[PDB]
Amino acid sequence: AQYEDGKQYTTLEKPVAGAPQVLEFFSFFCPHCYQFEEVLHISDNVKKKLPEGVKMTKYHVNFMGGDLGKDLTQAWAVAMALGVEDKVTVPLFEGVQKTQTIRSASDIRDVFINAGIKGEEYDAAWNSFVVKSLVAQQEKAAADVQLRGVPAMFVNGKYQLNPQGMDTSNMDVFVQQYADTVKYLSEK
């Protein structure tokens, strides 16, 4: 076939019922994740090719960066709750991996402040039980699917993208192959 199991994707032994249609996992500490967001714009190019009616979910993971890694999963929960994902993603990535100015929960908070989220609004979100269940959701979805590495994408809890098996000689070609694969898995 042109799309083969074990080649552009793998299949989960243990399929996850009730899973989001397209489920991406990342960490702000994750170097290929920085590339996927900043240089490749994977998430966005996948959207542009996905069928009608399909929702995209993106979650942060705890297993990188220890205490800060966990802080970042909670901050990402704040981001989802307030709908400000598109305003903090870039400065969080650069603050962790480029400038290395993120070292504490207080520094993560600064990024939201500078992006124009109000202090009171951030701290109230941060401490809210809506955010705690959102953190719970991120952890459960990761737990449901075996996850020990990022970036990772899962389609309907059955198929996992396998970027190792796509040519990286061209960045644009890589992205299209990636997105077309998601769409193929989507229609499966």
Image: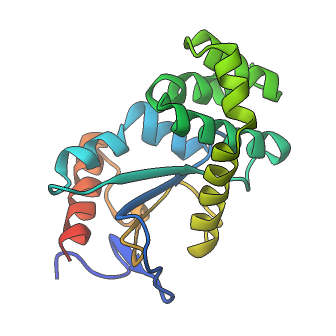
Camera-side residue of 58 and 122: 122
Camera-side residue of 98 and 184: 184
The residue lying at 57 percent from left, 56 percent from top is 150
What is the quadrant of residue 125 in the picture? top right
Q: Is residue 123 left or right of residue 86?
A: right
Q: Could you say where residue 40 lies in the image, as x and y percent from the top left? A: 36, 38
The residue lying at 25 percent from left, 41 percent from top is 172
Can residue 41 be spotted in the picture?
Answer: yes
Camera-side residue of 38 and 158: 158
Q: Is residue 6 left or right of residue 61?
A: left
Q: Quadrant of the C terminus?
A: bottom left
Q: Quadrant of the N terminus?
A: bottom left
The residue lying at 51 percent from left, 25 percent from top is 90
Q: How is the image coloured?
A: rainbow
Q: Could you say where residue 26 lies in the image, as x and y percent from the top left? A: 56, 49
What is the quadrant of residue 157 in the picture? bottom left
Q: Could you say where residue 11 lies in the image, as x and y percent from the top left? A: 41, 82
Name above or below for residue 14 compared with residue 101: below
Name above or below for residue 66 compared with residue 94: below
What is the quadrant of residue 7 in the picture? bottom left
Can residue 146 be spotted in the picture?
Answer: no
Q: Could you say where residue 28 lies in the image, as x and y percent from the top left? A: 63, 39
Name above or below for residue 188 compared with residue 166: below
Q: Is residue 77 left or right of residue 19?
A: right
Q: Is residue 182 left or right of residue 133?
A: left
The residue lying at 44 percent from left, 37 percent from top is 37
Name above or below for residue 114 compared with residue 171: above
- Count of numbered tags: 0
